[PDB]
Image (tube, coloured by chain):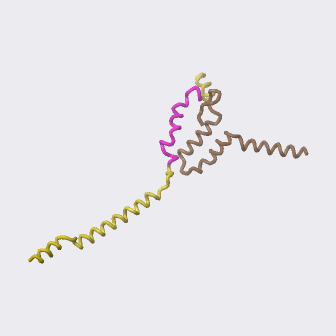
Chain colours: A yellow, B brown
């Protein structure tokens, strides 16, 4: 009965071939999906397309529109007309 | 270019600079503002106008010769 117990213990050891194959397939599919995702992540250029339209990059326009009435940068005719009216 | 002029008034072509900046902010492609960038640089350095005056002067001098 010692050999029978040893065989049962060895069978309790090892791994289920069905579970091993399923895990292998799942792991390979996951790696393939993630690697194509990382390749498309790397494919993007460093300079974005819309960077010239971004609000953060176009920060001078708002400030200068706010500050356009300061005497240091006024159009002379604007000052003339505001004096006239 | 900032609008702070050298004599306390509006800059010489801060208006040109702002036209170029608005074009760049609202443009689909940066080459669309090539004309306005050329205008801003031409105001900055007067290169094209000076070249035109120089070739007019050259023609005048060579006609004299």
Residue A43 falls left or right of residue B32: left
What segment is highlighted magenta in the picture?
A51-73
In the picture, residue B23 is in which quadrant?
top right
**Which secondary structure is most common in the magenta stretch?**
helix
User: At 30% across and 69% down in the image, what residue appears?
Assistant: A24
Q: From the viewer's perspective, is A15 left or right of B8?
A: left
What residue is at 49 percent from the left and 52 percent from the top? A46
Residue furthest toward the right?
A: B65
Occupied quadrant, residue A4: bottom left
Q: Residue at x 83, y 45 (%)?
A: B58
Residue A23: image x %, image y %? Answer: 27, 68
Looking at the rendered image, the quarter that the C terminus of chain A falls into is top right
Q: In this view, does B34 lie above or below A71?
A: below
**Which is more toward the observer, A20 or A34?**
A20
- Residue at 50% over, 48% down: A51
Task: Please name whichever residue, B51 or B15, is drawn nearer the observer in this view of the structure.
Answer: B51
Q: In this view, does B52 lie above or below A5?
A: above
Q: In the image, residue A62 lies at what x, y percent?
A: 50, 36
Residue A30 coordinates in the image, percent (x, y): 33, 64
Residue B40, how many percent across, how many down?
64, 41
- Name the residue furthest front: A2
Q: How many marks?
A: 0
Q: Is residue A68 above or below residue A45?
A: above
């Amino acid at each position: 009965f010692i050999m029978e117990f040893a065989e049962n213990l060895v069978l309790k050891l090892m791994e289920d071939p069905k579970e091993r194959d399923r895990r292998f397939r799942e792991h390979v599919y996951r790696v393939k999906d993630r690697c194509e995702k990382t390749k498309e992540m790397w494919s993007y250029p460093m300079r974005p397309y819309g960077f010239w339209t971004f609000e953060r990059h176009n920060s001078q326009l708002a400030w200068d529109a706010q500050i356009s009435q300061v005497p240091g940068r006024r159009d002379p005719y604007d000052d003339l007309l505001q004096h006239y009216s | 270019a900032s609008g702070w002029g050298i004599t306390g008034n509006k800059g010489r072509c801060y208006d040109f600079w702002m036209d170029f900046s608005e074009c760049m902010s609202r443009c689909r492609e940066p080459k669309d503002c090539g004309l306005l960038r050329e205008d801003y640089l031409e105001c900055l350095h007067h290169s094209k106008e000076f070249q035109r005056r120089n070739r007019i002067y050259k023609e005048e001098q060579r006609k004299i010769r």
